[PDB]
Image (cartoon, rainbow, N blue to C red; front, side, top):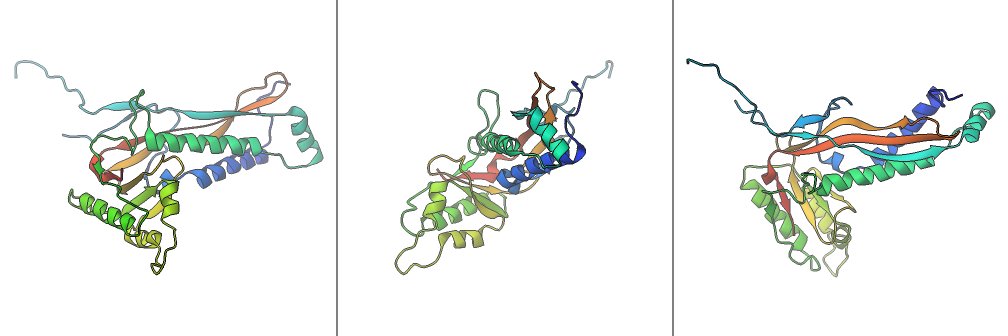
Length: 263
């Protein structure tokens, strides 16, 4: 009675679609970053940089750096009588716990993307060495956000990065960009959307009053994914069934000067 697969193919597919739909609904960075992969679950180490080209033998060693790929996961539990009822009474199965686990995993992925981990030697878009900086200014009065975005665009342009550009902002700035004033009547969010072709987005992971403008391109930054978010069975403990939702990816920043941060 221990078995290997407590569910059927249709239930497996339905759970996987639920998880992937939650992940695609929740993730933000995948709208601004390119994908290198999937490479496979057996790949654990990835290069970080780009390859640059007598009377005894010679020894050659690669000058590139390498990094290991981490894993993100979250667990949940299912009931054997519920599974039996679903199988015998021809009812659909409930996947709310799987949806919540996928949402938590997506939140953790976004946190790792935007801030990384200093203890493990991981860098984020907001803490990378070599990025450009633009003073925030005063967004309470009209014009500050547009001026800051224009200045950031100019500074990115002067370093040989010509766009198109993407903008990510904190909830406070995003809400401040939608204010209505007397005889101003034009949305700074609309003007910034017109200016930035790749898009303007809001993320709750950003803290306080902060924002980032990035120049897209595979030769500046990307995301290497070994295994996309998926669910697995951990084996029956007692008679209930445990499952785990997990994924594996890493962020590679090759040109730090394509990122500008607005205080």
